[PDB]
Image (cartoon, rainbow, N blue to C red; front, top):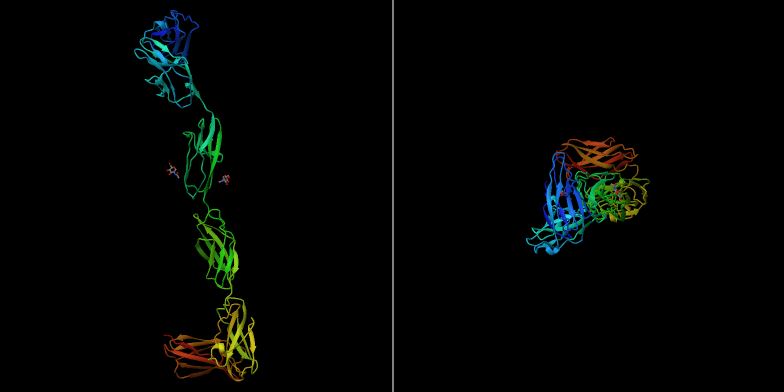
Amino acid sequence: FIKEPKDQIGVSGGVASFVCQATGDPKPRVTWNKKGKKVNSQRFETIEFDESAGAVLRIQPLRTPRDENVYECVAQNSVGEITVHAKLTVLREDQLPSGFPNIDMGPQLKVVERTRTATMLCAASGNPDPEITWFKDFLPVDPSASNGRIKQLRSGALQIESSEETDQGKYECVATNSAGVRYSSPANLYVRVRRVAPRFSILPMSHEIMPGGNVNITCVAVGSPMPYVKWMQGAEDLTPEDDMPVGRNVLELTDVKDSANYTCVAMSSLGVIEAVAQITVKSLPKAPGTPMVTENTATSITITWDSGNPDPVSYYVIEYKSKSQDGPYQIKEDITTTRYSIGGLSPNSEYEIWVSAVNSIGQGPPSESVVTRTGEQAPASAPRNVQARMLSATTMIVQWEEPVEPNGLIRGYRVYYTMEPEHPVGNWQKHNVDDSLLTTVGSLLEDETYTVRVLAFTSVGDGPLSDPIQVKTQQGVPGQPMNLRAEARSETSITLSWSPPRQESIIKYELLFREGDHGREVGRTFDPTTSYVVEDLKPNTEYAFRLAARSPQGLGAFTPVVRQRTLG
Ligand SMILES: *[C@@H]1O[C@H](CO)[C@@H](O)[C@H](O)[C@H]1NC(C)=O
Ligand SMILES: *[C@@H]1O[C@H](CO)[C@@H](O)[C@H](O)[C@H]1NC(C)=O
C-alpha cells in the first residue's frame, strides 16, 4: 500500500472520499467492503483508477448514524493479501467545534483556453488552519505527478500552469484538519479549443542575389492547431521530420547559381496553405535596342539609344567599324548616358554602329546596328600624275588621276597655268572643269615653257594644288620627265630614277648636276632608261640634279631641281 486511508470526521449532508492504492507483482484488483461483504447502497459509490489498482470510496450525502463504520480496503494479487481499515465519523452542523473547517470561498465555474493557465480558487478557515486537498471527477489530484505544472498555493488556490483537454472536469476543494473535513460545492473547469485554420505571420520573401550568392528565406505560420512549417522545391520537400520546427522555419541557402522557386508549406490537421518566394539570380543585361543618329559632321557621328533594360545599367559600350573599308572594330567604354558623340572619324565614310550595356554581372549582347555616313570636306590631297603635252603649236592637253583623299563627292577640278611661275598661283590663269580627268587649253604662246598646277574640289571647298609640272610649247620634243627620285646608293654614289615616258621616242637623256649650290655643272648624255647611277661622288655632301629627254626635234623640258646627298 503506497497510500493508506485516514480516519475521517465529516458533516451531515457533506462528502467523504477514502483513498486506497496498492502496488506490486502481480498487480492487484482492490475493493471496498463494510462488515466483510460489500453491502452496497444508493448514496455510496466506488471510482476505480489505475486499472482497478487503486480505488476511491465516495459517500454523499453523509448521514448519521447510518454511515459511521470502519471500512475495509481489500488488496490481493497471486502472491499475498492484506487489508487496511479506516473509520468514518459523521457529525451534524449544530455539533461542530468552532474550529471546524469552513469554506469561505470555494471554486468558481471557470473557462480558459489551452496552454493558458487556470487558477481554481479555494479559501478556508479553522483552528488549526486547514490543509487543502482537491478532487477532480471524484478522484484526488497530486501536484507532484504533474511535473510541477500543477501546484497548491498556501493562500488557497490550485494553479494549472498549462491547460490541456484532460484538465476539464468537476473540481472539489477540501479543507482538512484535526477537527475533520469539509468539501466545497463543485465547480467545472472548461478548457476550450479554439479552431483557427493556419495563416502566415511572415510570408516567404522573394529575392534577387548575385551568383553564389546566399540568402535566408524566413517563413512564419500561425494557427490552432499551431501549424508545422516545411520547405518544397516543386513537388519535393527539403526539410526532414526528425526535428521539423513548428511556427517558424528559415531556409539558409548558400552558393546559388540557378534561379529557382521555393514553396513554404504550412500544414496542420485543420488545413494546408502555401506561399512561394522566387529566388532570381541577377543576369547579364539585354540588348540596348537600335541606336539612332541625331547629328553628322565631317569627323563625327552622334547618337542616342533606349536603355533596353528594365533594371538600371552601370554603363554602355559602343563598338563600330568603317563599312567602307571593312575593319577594324573600335570601342568606347564607360559611357554613362544614352547619348554619345563618336569623334575622330574620317569624312565621307560610312560606319556601322552597335551598342551594348554593362551591369554588375557583366556586358550584355549588342543592339541591332545603325549604318550612317560622315559629312563632306575639302580634299586633303592633290590630283596625281598630272601630265601635259601639246596637240598643236598653241594648245595643250592636261590629264590627271583623282586624289587619294577627296573627303567627298568631287564636283570638279581647277587648272592653274602660266609661264611666269614666280608669281603667286592665285594670279595665274585658271579655269574650272567637271569631275572628268582630262581637259585642253589653247591660246598659248608658241615656243615657251608653261608650268601647270591642278587642284580638286567638292561642295565644301578647294584641295591642295599638285606640285608644279611644266611643259614646252615647241612640239616634237618629249615631255618633262616624271616623278624624278634620287636616293643614296653608297657613301660615294646616288641612284636617280623616274617613271617610264609616254609614247614619245626619246633618242637620249640629258642629265645635269652640281656639287651643292656653287659647284661645277657636270653634264651627261646616255641611252634611254628609267634610272641612272651617279658614280664617284663625295661622302656626306649634297648634290642637285635635273633631267630632260631628247627627241629628233630637240630637247624636252627639264625636271625641277631634285637634291640628294651621299651616305653619311
Ligand atoms: C542566415 O542565417 C545564418 C545562421 O544564423 C547566419 O550566419 C547568416 O548571417 C544569415 N544570413 C542572412 C543573409 O540572413
Ligand atoms: C517560378 O514561378 C513563377 C510564377 O510566376 C514564374 O514566373 C517563374 O518563371 C518561375 N521560375 C522558375 C525558376 O521556375
